[PDB]
Image (cartoon, rainbow, N blue to C red):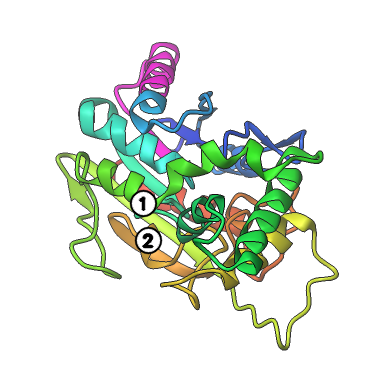
Amino acid sequence: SSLKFPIVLVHGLLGFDKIGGIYPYFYGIKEALEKAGAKVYIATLSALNSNELRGEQLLEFVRKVQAETGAAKVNLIGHSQGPLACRYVAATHPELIASVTSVNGVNHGSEVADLVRLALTPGRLPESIANAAMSAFGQLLSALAGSPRLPQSGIEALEALTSEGVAAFNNKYPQGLPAEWGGEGKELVNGVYYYSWSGVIDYNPLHQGANNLDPLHVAMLAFSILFTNERFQNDGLVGRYSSHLGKVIGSDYSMDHVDAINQLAGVVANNTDPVQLFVEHVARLKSKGL
């Protein structure tokens, strides 16, 4: 092992243990992290909206890793909703956490989640816009499940991504958060290292098509248009500045939301190598004494 502490991967995307139905969440990432000389464990969590409850499940898994390895701490690496569970464990039990790495994390909420909830009230939004948010969401759910899913079967899980919901969490566990919109947070807080990286897409509907992409990436293109604040800087589910946590290694990579975890099945829709970012991060953690 090149690292002093093991790595625990934390998934968190609308309650899916695996993408497409069979494909592992962090596709080809565990094998790559191990190839860099690191011990990797995949956290098993339940589809909950409470990051405190999901965090407790993560806390249990971490203590099981420590029992098997004999290590004092672990390096937390989470995706999307994942980092929120990581931030909880680091806040309540910093003595067990060496570092918290956020990958396209929903650290300040999702503008997509704020839009879809408004489509439940007939009249709150223009009918065309409301149907567009529900249609794209249904396309996302179907791709993630690998089978036809109605958007109403994923609304509850999407509620956990709202700006109001995350803001309540942030006010209770603000460790590592930026002091200003677009800025960075402290790299080292209470003996815990905080890192983050994310991506944005360069998609113009008037010049770029979407007939050669998997429906999983197509949904990202549709939602990126429906962004209100970070309209020209998001990965399809979370804006660039919304994903900042601790030291921002880079939040403007060429990745959509599912590109960050090498989906679908290694077939990314953009230019940035997702796996290499994880590999290079191993060297970063190693040089920090982690």
Tag shown at residue 242 = 2
Q: Earlier in the sequence, mark 1 or mark 2?
A: 1
In percent of the image, x 30 and y 29: which residue is there? 89
The answer to whether one can see residue 286 in this image is no
Q: Position of residue 257 (x, y in %)?
A: 58, 57
Q: Position of residue 199 (x, y in %)?
A: 51, 65
Indicate whether 165 appears above or below 15: below
Tag shown at residue 229 = none
Extent of the magenta region: 56-77
**Is 7 left or right of 120, judged from the image as shown?**
left
Quickly name the residue at label 1.
Answer: 107
- Which amino acid lies under the numbered mark 1 shown in the image of this protein? Asn
The quarter holding residue 229 reads: bottom left
Q: Tag 2, which secondary structure?
A: helix
- Which amino acid lies under the numbered mark 2 shown in the image of this protein? Ser
Q: Position of residue 5 (x, y in %)?
A: 37, 31
In reply to whether residue 178 is colored magenta, the answer given is no
View extreme (front): residue: 123
